[PDB]
Image (cartoon, coloured by chain):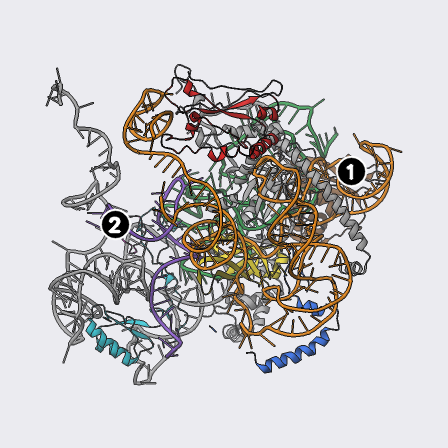
Chain colours: A cyan, D blue, E red, F brown, G yellow, I purple, J green, L orange
RNA sequence: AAUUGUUGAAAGGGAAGGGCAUUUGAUCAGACAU
RNA sequence: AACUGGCGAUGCGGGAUGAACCGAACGUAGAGUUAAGGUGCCGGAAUACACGCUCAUCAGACACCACAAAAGGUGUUAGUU
RNA sequence: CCCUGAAAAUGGAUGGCGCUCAAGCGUGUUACCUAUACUCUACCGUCAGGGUUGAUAUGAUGCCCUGACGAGUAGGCAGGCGUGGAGGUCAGUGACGAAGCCUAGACCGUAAGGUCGGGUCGAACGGCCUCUAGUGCAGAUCUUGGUGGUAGUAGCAAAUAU
RNA sequence: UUUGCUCCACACAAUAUAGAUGGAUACGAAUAAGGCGUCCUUGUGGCGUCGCUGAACCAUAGCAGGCUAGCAACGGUGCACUUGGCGGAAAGGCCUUGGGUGCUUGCUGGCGAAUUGCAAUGUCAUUUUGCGUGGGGAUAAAUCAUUUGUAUACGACUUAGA
């Protein structure tokens, strides 16, 4: 029960990994553009890891939309869950990670009453 | 360059398929006669066939008509260039130079 | 089109036969080449012997067991000529070369089957008459093949047995042709003639 | 994990019984329709007429 | 050249049967039991094998062993070796 | 290049000093009209003091052969620039048309002297109709009375990669 | 009958490739019958199946099929181009392929 | 640079590799070329040095 | 974290690692259920 | 040193291989046509068609490029006088 | 065209196989193969030219239309992501478990990174508008600290002998 | 060595497949020559015919190939047996006898198909293993340790010990 949207096309996947992150443990996997002179990644040689460019940008109509067709909106309590009463088919509530279970039960009850979709209803549930 | 003298058929097909204007420094497509009348109504060029006429018969406002026409972006010739190596003069068995009457086939293939 | 295609090696040119067989093998056809001792190479015997001697001269300096292995049997010579044509260093090439068997003479598993020839790779079709050519068996026994005579004697025995079989086949085929001839001119044969049979 | 319409079976029995007489006017059409088509070795569908 | 078949004698001496074991002292010494039993019923299989050798045998070699017990050597395990017969045709060699 | 023979008439550009100039005509064997005109201007440039920027082509018309079926013996005179110097040659070719004769001349000259089209001048191709005007044995050989020769050792192109019987080359 | 085949047999040759770069999206199929692009032009719209077997039984069978279609002719030897829903595995070069007659035009 | 003074190579290169024998009894690699005229006889014997 | 042990999975004919594409195995979200 | 174009700062197809050469300069994708270069096999593409030459007991095989000369041959072919 | 002239050192290179009415040389005509090139389309971004006051789901820095373009070291500028700390705010999260840490489990962004589930854990921490800086590491024979293959290896053999 | 091992038949399950989906259909030799039929004086003979591609030949109709009736022949074919040979180059196959049984679309009939819904490989092959069935069949070595020296750095090698 979400807003109709065109096909979600991801121009790229396989998260851009830092060069030599596989080779060296000190090199983290977060992307960093190579600044070296004789670098086969800065000079886009054939057979090397692709670099993030603006051309990979997702469609402005399908941007930020989850596969369910909503945009995830963080909620910390019922007061900010109520911000999605009139936008049920565009925004989906996502309970924050630091919310206690005895508050998440209340949040889930209120959201199911209001029709708001919660993307993480199985959080800290002691069932 | 490869250049020749195009026939009326080549000119008409070019203007109909890849005819683009130069309205307000923007390359708009020659979709309706209204677009041509808006800009070239000063010179009497009222229709796309008016434009084709002022092109084929070099007329009083040929400079203006041809300038209004945007540089045609032609594809590669279907079926190749008919030659193993382009960069020799057409007289020398190549592709460039004054092909004269043979330009029609090349332009139709490249359209 | 059959699962295993047996190629009669006699009269064929090594390079062209190998170039055909490599493409077929990569295409997936299982190929068994027989009669490798009577393959043909263009050029005269001394020229081809000099080429093979120049090939023999090339070996690893510091350890000859690591160098090129100069196989001398005709089957292995043709197999080397084909492995040079097939990209053998990859799994695709290894599967292709696994799909291939090369023999000298005709072994018992394949002497009862139908041997085909490749017209694009035949000496009598590709070489202009008057051009000198070599027999792979002669070249091999010159450069050190130890089994020319023990293969020739087995070829003699195989050809003798095959002649005994072919006499019976020819007799039975003549009987079949005669019997089919009597059934010709009949109603069903006349009806088949209009349809092409 | 676990019948035919009677109307449908009667229409089939009348259409096929009306068509069988037309079939019988030619020698081998009934046997031909009983047979099932199948490409044989060496068949060229680009050159096989139908 | 490839060996086709070997036909052994009915009775093998202990010093040559030792060649077929590494632990003769505790072995059951079963070598050639079900083969010396094949010489029973006038050795039909043995003569058939010899006939096949005559039919297809280009070179004939004989397995022999030394009576090493006659030597002063301490080793009682004899040596077995193939010596080629040079002489008449294959039938003569195998008959010999 | 499957040449077509063109006959091209041109002249100098008329002026008030001497209007109505002298028409000059040439026969050029070329692949098409463009190359025909280019060769015409080349030859006029090397013959008289006139270049295309100073003259004009009044006409260019293709010549088709009078009898494209009757087999003739053309005698051709041709000069060419070898790797060291220029030589004049006479060769005769037995063919069917002037354009075919010029084409086989070009192939033959390229094959026997490595002379590309850029370094060959066709001096003159003229049909010789009387026999015994023939002087090259490779053409005198085919004028024999009641000529018949065989074609031994025929090899058939195979439409399939495998032939199932060992072929014979009879004929 | 003993033959139930309703498809033309074919061999999966290779992906479309330059000298040193291969495009896995477009494969090449050599049909056993065709020997020229003129004859290959008949099979352009035909559906193609690569039929393989796996040890795990899913959706009722251990036989799985990757579908595709002929797209256009390739070369002068009757080879055809093929586009599949999921590109054929590179392990299936020289593997067998069923080119069905549907959709048909006769 | 070339070897200043020539000298024959040490050892024989046709006896390589200088590893141990496969077994304590050396194999008779070759046998006399058989002819079918003389009577049947052995072409070797075993002894102990 | 480097580094190490056991268990589990997988691969391994003189490196390992990587990119594109898919087969295979394992694993997983969403949606019809509205 | 002069002019221009490049490489440096530049990846891509080709020249097997290479900073400079040939084609061509780049957002991410899909389809179509080509450039340079190629179509026996490795290798995707005609063991195409056509006319001739060459047999080397060190052939020849593609520009920059990974060389060959003066002088000779009754090897052979086409020519001139 | 071919041959002699033509001699260099590890084994060896028309790229290799191999090729002889060629898969060689000279030439001609077609067909065909494919680049991040060309043509058309979609999308991302940039630039430029424009439309939009109507109360406004607000915000004119918003929404929308049209066209072209997109390589790049040194360098310049812009828009952003992240960290310690400060003012304001969310009467924010939290012993019913904050922070941290592990997580070939999930989602979002082209990316910097952001969010969620699971385990461990025990007491503080975050979103936004701004302010401030001792604010972002792969290198510096970097500093300190810790740990590897080498490797159960070199070796533990002078001075008489147990 | 206490029901371990091998083989035979089917039964289930697992296991994968370099890739069944009518048949790999057997002279030899030359190509400026052969194949086949035929005749005789048997020859390097005569005569005739064929090639110009396997586009062939064989097989091919039935529930993925059902149940039934008859006609005409005494054939063709599968299967399990049986008889006798040939084959050692990687023989592991090729022929052959006899009857039994099954089918026979060589020819004429009778009944069934539906509904997998307009297609979805719509699953029919063989490769290995394991456990069961019930039926046979056969009842050892090697190594450590000790020992010798024809050997040896240690492994290894060569010996001997109920």
Q: Which residue is mark 2?
A: A26
Q: Which residue is mark 1?
A: F139
Q: Are marks 2 and 1 on the same chain?
A: no
Quadrant of residue J59 within the rendered picture: top right
Whether residue C196 appears in magenta in the rendering, the answer is no
Answer yes or no: is residue H24 visible: yes
Residue H21 is situated, as x and y percent measured from the top left of the image, at: 41, 25
Answer yes or no: is residue B3 visible: no
Residue C76 is situated, as x and y percent measured from the top left of the image, at: 54, 35
Is F58 on the left or on the right of E54, as rendered? Answer: right
Measure the alpha-carbon separation of dots 2 and 1: 86 Å
In the image, C167 versus F111, the foreground residue is C167
Label 2 is found on which chain of the structure?
A
In the image, L141 versus F49, the foreground residue is L141
Up the image or down, H36 lies above or below D43; here it is above
Residue range highlighted in magenta = A23-31
């Amino acid at each position: 029960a979400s807003l109709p949207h065109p096909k979600i096309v991801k121009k790229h996947t396989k998260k851009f990994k830092r060069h030599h992150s596989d080779r060296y443990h000190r090199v983290a996997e977060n992307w960093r553009k190579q600044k070296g002179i004789d670098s086969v990644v800065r000079r886009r040689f054939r057979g090397n890891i692709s670099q993030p460019k603006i051309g990979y940008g997702s469609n402005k109509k399908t941007k930020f939309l989850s596969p369910s067709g909503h945009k995830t909106f963080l909620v910390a309590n019922v007061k900010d869950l109520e911000t999605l009463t009139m936008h049920t088919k565009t925004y989906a509530a996502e309970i924050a990670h630091n919310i206690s279970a005895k508050n998440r039960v209340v949040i889930l009850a209120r959201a199911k009453a209001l029709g708001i979709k919660v993307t993480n209803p199985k959080g800290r549930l002691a069932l | 360059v490869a250049y020749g003298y195009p026939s009326y058929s080549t000119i008409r097909q070019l203007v109909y398929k890849r005819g683009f204007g130069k309205i307000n420094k923007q390359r708009v497509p020659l979709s309706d006669n209204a677009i041509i009348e808006a800009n070239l109504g000063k010179y009497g060029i009222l229709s796309i066939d008016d434009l084709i006429h002022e092109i084929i018969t070099v007329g009083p406002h040929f400079k203006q008509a041809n300038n209004f026409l945007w540089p045609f972006k032609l594809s590669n010739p279907s079926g190749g260039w008919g030659v193993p190596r382009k960069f020799k003069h057409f007289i020398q068995g190549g592709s460039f130079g004054n092909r004269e009457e043979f330009i029609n086939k090349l332009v139709k293939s490249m359209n | 089109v059959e699962p295993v295609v047996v190629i009669d090696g006699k009269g064929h040119l090594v390079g062209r036969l190998a170039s055909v067989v490599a493409k077929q093998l990569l295409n997936g056809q299982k190929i068994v080449v027989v009669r490798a001792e009577e393959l043909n190479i263009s050029g005269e015997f001394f020229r081809n012997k000099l080429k093979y001697h120049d090939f023999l001269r090339k070996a690893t300096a510091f350890n000859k067991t690591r160098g090129p292995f100069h196989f001398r049997a005709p089957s292995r010579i043709f197999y080397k000529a084909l492995r040079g044509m097939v990209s053998h260093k990859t799994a695709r090439g290894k599967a292709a070369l696994e799909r291939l068997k090369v023999f000298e003479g005709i072994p018992p598993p394949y002497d009862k089957k139908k041997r085909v020839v490749v017209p694009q790779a035949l000496r009598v079709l590709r070489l202009k008459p008057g051009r000198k050519y070599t027999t792979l068996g002669k070249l091999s026994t010159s450069v050190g093949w130890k089994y020319e005579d023990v293969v020739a004697k087995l070829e003699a025995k195989r050809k003798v047995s095959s002649a005994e079989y072919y006499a019976k086949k020819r007799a039975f085929t003549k009987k079949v042709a005669s019997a089919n001839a009597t059934a010709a001119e009949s109603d069903v044969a006349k009806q088949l003639a209009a349809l092409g049979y | 994990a676990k019948e035919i319409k009677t109307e449908r079976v009667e229409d089939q029995k009348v259409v096929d019984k009306a068509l069988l007489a037309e079939i019988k006017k030619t020698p081998l059409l009934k046997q031909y329709l009983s047979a099932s088509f199948s490409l044989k070795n060496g068949d060229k569908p680009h050159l096989l007429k139908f | 050249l490839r060996s086709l078949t070997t036909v052994w004698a009915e009775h093998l001496s202990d010093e040559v049967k030792r060649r077929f074991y590494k632990n003769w002292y505790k072995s059951k010494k079963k070598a050639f039991t079900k083969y010396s039993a094949k010489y029973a019923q006038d050795g039909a299989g043995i003569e058939r094998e010899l006939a096949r050798i005559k039919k297809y045998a280009s070179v004939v070699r004989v397995l022999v062993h030394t009576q090493i017990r006659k030597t002063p050597l301490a080793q009682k395990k004899a040596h077995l070796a193939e010596i080629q017969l040079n002489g008449g045709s294959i039938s003569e060699k195998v008959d010999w | 290049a499957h040449f077509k023979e063109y006959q091209v008439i041109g002249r100098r550009l008329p002026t008030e000093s001497v209007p109505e100039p002298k028409l000059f005509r040439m026969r050029i064997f070329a692949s098409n009209e463009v190359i025909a005109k280019s060769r015409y201007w080349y030859f006029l440039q090397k013959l008289h003091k006139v270049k295309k920027a100073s003259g004009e082509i009044v006409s260019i018309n293709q010549i088709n052969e009078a009898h494209p079926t009757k087999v003739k013996n053309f005698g051709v005179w041709v000069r060419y620039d070898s790797r060291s110097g220029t030589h004049n040659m006479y060769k005769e070719i037995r063919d069917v048309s002037r354009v075919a004769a010029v084409e086989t001349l070009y192939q033959d000259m390229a094959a026997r002297h490595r002379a590309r089209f850029r370094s060959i001048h066709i001096l003159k191709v003229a049909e010789i109709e009387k026999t015994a005007d023939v002087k090259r044995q490779y053409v005198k050989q085919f004028l024999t009375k009641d000529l018949k020769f065989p074609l031994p050792h025929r090899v058939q192109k195979s439409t399939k990669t495998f032939s199932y019987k060992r072929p014979s080359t009879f004929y | 009958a003993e033959s139930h085949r309703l498809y033309v047999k074919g061999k999966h040759l290779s992906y479309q490739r330059s000298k040193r770069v291969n495009n896995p999206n477009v494969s090449l199929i050599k049909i056993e019958g065709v020997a020229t692009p003129q004859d290959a032009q008949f099979y352009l719209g035909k559906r193609i199946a690569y039929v393989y077997r796996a040890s795990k039984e899913v959706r009722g069978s251990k036989i799985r099929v990757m579908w595709g279609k002929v797209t256009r002719t390739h070369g002068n030897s009757g080879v055809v181009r093929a586009t599949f829903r999921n590109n054929l595995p590179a392990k299936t070069f020289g593997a067998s392929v069923r080119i069905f007659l549907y959709p048909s035009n006769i | 640079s070339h070897r200043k003074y020539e000298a024959p190579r040490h050892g024989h290169l046709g006896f390589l590799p200088r590893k141990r024998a496969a077994s304590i009894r050396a194999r008779v690699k070759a046998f006399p070329k058989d002819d079918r005229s003389k009577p049947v006889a052995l072409t070797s014997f075993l002894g102990y040095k």
